[PDB]
Amino acid sequence: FDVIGGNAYTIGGRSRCSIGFAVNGGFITAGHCGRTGATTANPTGTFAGSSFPGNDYAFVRTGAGVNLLAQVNNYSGGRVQVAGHTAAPVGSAVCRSGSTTGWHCGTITALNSSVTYPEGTVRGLIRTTVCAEPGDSGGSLLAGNQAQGVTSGGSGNCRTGGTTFFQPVNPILQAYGLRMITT
Image: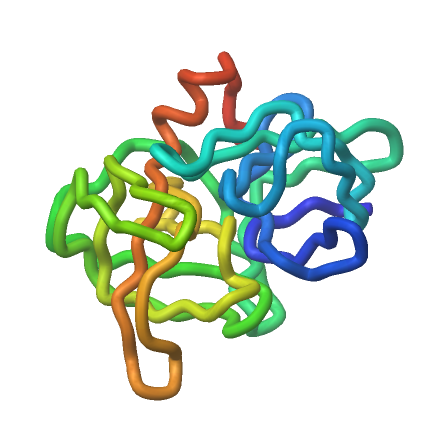
């Protein structure tokens, strides 16, 4: 089974979230998607660290038969190569891949933003003009070929527009001592 950024995965049968990025040992996604020990399908895996609220990140460990690719689905029948994870500055054009709305782009308008979800406050977020809908959570945010973050949440939708916040990738890699797959 191929793990590609932006694709749906399921948790207890529910397509709640999208894949963020492939890393050594599995993939990273949003913490609100599930708690440590929860199991996924497509791909088969287990949450092996989750931080939400406060942060919004998680790592899902995958095992045999799962190919971890340095790619993000562009939802036009192609893939985008993930080349690194150098953070882009405010004003940068960024595109999000998620399993509900596909590929949508916008610009970074703030860093270290806070939002208050029903569950509590999440801080340290990338604020953007990219739209997202439920199902897109956990999905990839790219500036060109550089991983920026995974979809956390926001307001609005892709029909009328909205504001979407992303958990930056660097703190996730640091939290779990992970390296992004490049090849």
